[PDB]
Image (cartoon, rainbow over all chains, first blue to last red; front, side, top):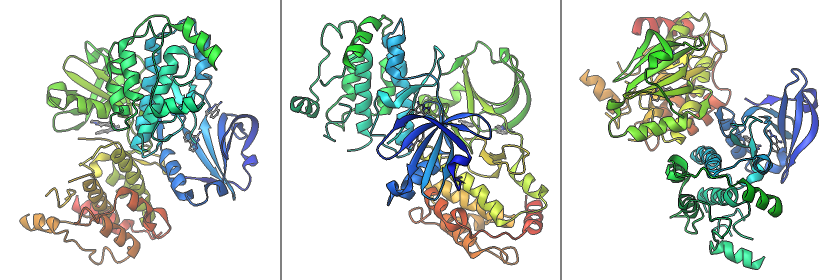
Amino acid sequence: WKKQAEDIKKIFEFKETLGTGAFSEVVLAEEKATGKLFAVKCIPKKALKGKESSIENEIAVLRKIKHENIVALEDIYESPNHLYLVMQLVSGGELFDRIVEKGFYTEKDASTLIRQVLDAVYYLHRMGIVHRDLKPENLLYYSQDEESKIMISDFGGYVAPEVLYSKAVDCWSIGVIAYILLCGYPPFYDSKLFEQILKAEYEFDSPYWDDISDSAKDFIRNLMEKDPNKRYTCEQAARHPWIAGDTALNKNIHESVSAQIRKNF
Amino acid sequence: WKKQAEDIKKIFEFKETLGTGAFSEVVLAEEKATGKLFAVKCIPKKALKGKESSIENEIAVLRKIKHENIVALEDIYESPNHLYLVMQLVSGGELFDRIVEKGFYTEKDASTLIRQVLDAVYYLHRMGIVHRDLKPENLLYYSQDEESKIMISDFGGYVAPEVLYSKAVDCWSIGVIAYILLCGYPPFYDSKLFEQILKAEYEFDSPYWDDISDSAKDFIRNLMEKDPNKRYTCEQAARHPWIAGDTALNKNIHESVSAQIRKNF
Ligand SMILES: Nc1nn2nccc2c2ccccc12
Ligand SMILES: Nc1nn2nccc2c2ccccc12
Ligand SMILES: Nc1nn2nccc2c2ccccc12
Ligand SMILES: Nc1nn2nccc2c2ccccc12
């Protein structure tokens, strides 16, 4: 299930660097035998010392499973001292860029995005994976298509008060993302910030929140809940009317949200 | 995520019946708009009364996930009184037919089959699904290819002593399947049979088991373990040398296994 290589460069022509992380890089790569483009995560083995097997079990299991809202692992290569995760390259661009570029953007659009993230994270949780790093940077659109889905592209403010813990920390992160999706700025924002987060002290301030539904605000409260016990799970969040029902509004909130994204990020 | 239809027959031409179950049928079907063949499971809604949502949640989640060793759910249609699960049609045929037809069959072949079933069932367990009905009839080859994988094709001797319970019942079933794969006959076989199962009384009888490895027998013992606590999980079984290592033998055991399948089934 792992392909072996004496030298990865016999298989891929590496191109531009797409991302860099703690102790890995993600690079764009052409498969020399086929032309096909991929995103390849490059990981030195010595960085995984100890929990090498455990992290090669997340990978061994995930290799066999394709989730609609997570970039698929097409292949794993092993050399003497590295693992290479060969991933489906997406073509739809970054989350905020997309929202800024839209002419029209509603709560229904935000709800659809969150629904997809909930589905992906529910799956990861079921598999015993706590993502711990859900944030906009790690969400990419699949394609340029108007109807493109969003996908978790990568694994390693958004951190749960208990951290500052269990799978519930991810659900907090999703709540923060939802907050940003509906107003264009983060719910917290240096010691007073740290203080705010640890007391889950945030507001739906005017004028930015005035045109947002009660249902959306309730949804966010239930995820951005200090008590990780009372906090909605992904399963609970997915049943909420804002996600599963028809309470998400159809008002164009693009002007304000985009203004705030531009100004705030 | 569910397509709605006033009449399913506007979408599919139904052909031969592929399977029948408790209160559903699986039928071969041509998509009229495209020609493409599928396997369609047809389910009256009233059969799911009560746990309708719950069973529509197994489906709602699974729709988004493709496992290499489970037939994929391509689409779900809903009419006023039925659900239709539209599945990827396989082309590789039934498990025993394939083994009888081979000229050469080894423990390594059996191990590869079990590895795949372990992977599928591990995933189902992680999702909170207990299959409860794992048996050869529910395993089909993907293609005619020599290297074809096996796939769970369907959901609803092989039943765990505790039943005669938890996800562990599936692991018992896999042990029974492994037993049959290595000798061509069931480990139990009417009141004395019921008695045997409830005491996990079985043997690796000569001459059929003489050419089988100790490693294979140990593997089977660990799954066909009366105590569901001590019983190997799918995760444990997948780490066993017979599956993960190189203890599976390379001896052609086809003559005997096929003889016994033919005679016994
Ligand atoms: N530009 C990127 N594209 N794709 N495509 C698949 C996976 C990724 C990815 C992962 C991490 C960082 C950047 C990217
Ligand atoms: N970009 C990814 N990075 N890492 N890092 C470890 C495991 C994974 C992974 C698995 C599936 C899809 C994407 C990725
Ligand atoms: N002959 C069959 N073929 N395929 N292909 C996909 C799923 C199934 C299936 C399920 C149940 C019963 C028979 C079959
Ligand atoms: N043949 C199947 N039958 N049923 N019945 C309920 C759920 C499913 C299912 C899901 C995925 C793949 C195959 C099937």
